[PDB]
Amino acid sequence: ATQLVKAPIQVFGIEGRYATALYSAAVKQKKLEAVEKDLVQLNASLKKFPRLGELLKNPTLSRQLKKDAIGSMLKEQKAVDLTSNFLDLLTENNRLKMVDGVINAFKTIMAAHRGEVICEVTSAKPLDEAARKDLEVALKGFLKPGQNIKLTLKTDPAIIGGLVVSIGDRFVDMSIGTKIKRYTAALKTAV
Amino acid sequence: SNGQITAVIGAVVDVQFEDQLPPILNALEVQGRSPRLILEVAQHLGENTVRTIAMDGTEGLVRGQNVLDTGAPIKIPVGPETLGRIMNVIGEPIDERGPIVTDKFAAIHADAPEFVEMSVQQEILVTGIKVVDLLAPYAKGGKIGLFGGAGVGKTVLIMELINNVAKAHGGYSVFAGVGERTREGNDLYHEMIESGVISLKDKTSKV
Amino acid sequence: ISAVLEEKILGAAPKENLEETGRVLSIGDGIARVYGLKNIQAEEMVEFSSGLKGMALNLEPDNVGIVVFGNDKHIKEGDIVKRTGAIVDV
Image (cartoon, rainbow over all chains, first blue to last red; front, side, top):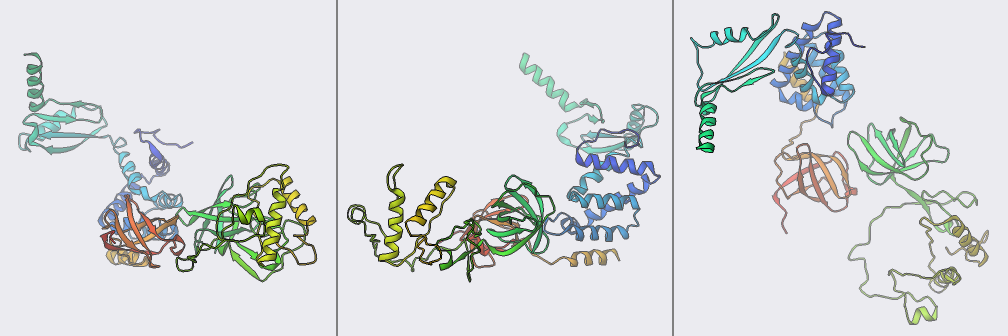
């Protein structure tokens, strides 16, 4: 049926079906990066003006007005034919109310396609200098060749100390706060 | 004022309009049915489509079929011309006696009389039947339960009520066979013809 | 240029104060669901375009379910419903 990289991720739902069809259409042609960047620009324009999102997600308004507004705001972004056909298909089936989902589903692709794995590191306090770069060096060896790391850093003083590291497949809770919490729980439940 | 059939599920038809949405209890006529199909709007579903109940059979309908909104509820013919005739729900004559040529049409959904339009005196409707007028009197505007089974003159009593009210008071009568059997309806119609309450070509009908 | 374009897109649609005004999505059997009335309170009386009264009983994320104090034949889909600003009182 559809010729692609045969689901680089496992994305589900009807919005996942639309995103995989758009990925197959944009990988049969050489327009994958163009449709990715105009969908990013479209999502940025929708988040910039919530009145446009309220106009699109209004059941009172007719679908012809919605597709006219979609084409009007895609002309100024200098879009391609593939994303115009994708948005016309979304507004034809009255599924443009979930236009935030498919783009997010399309953001879920081009992470495995580009090898980017999402990593989340949470610390008691934000650190730099001696930190950061050694964390990147440690995380670089956690991947097979051809993959990259997209790192998000968080701070939370409630974990007392240590580090909370989560990858897209596994989790490790090697933190001081959880360690002393389970040690005190063991001491209370035993002694 | 013109819509298209979206869904057909049993006697429930979902029809989608473009410009003007018909209100609740309005009648919509299907444009491809030779015995015309009138749909009554029961609720608004949003998205410019409404859910309707059918007044006739639904076999053979196709999606996208044109429906014309009448802009009014089911308007049935009313007048002295409907005396002695048999009508269906939508006012079509089903007694094979020709068309009902009248000048007055009325919607079957109207408002109740107000609190100031009601009489404070609970008057009785005298019907000329001695046992009824003495022991179980009929009140004007009341609800009356007529019991009786097979072999008793319940039909004869009904026709006597019709004749006595039309004679003593000058007021007509209306019979409504809500979900009645065809054999019982045919027997009632022929008994009404035989006893002279329904009269053909004389215009002296009382029901 | 882009902001003027989005202003034109917004102005292509009519201006409605959805906080205090609502449009009837569906009216029937004395119960009307309305799009709008973002500042409505629970059990709050509302007025319709025909002069009828209603009570906002259901506060749903998409619509507001209002029980109509009268016959629903005078209310059409797309009519204007406005808040009275107060809970139902006699």
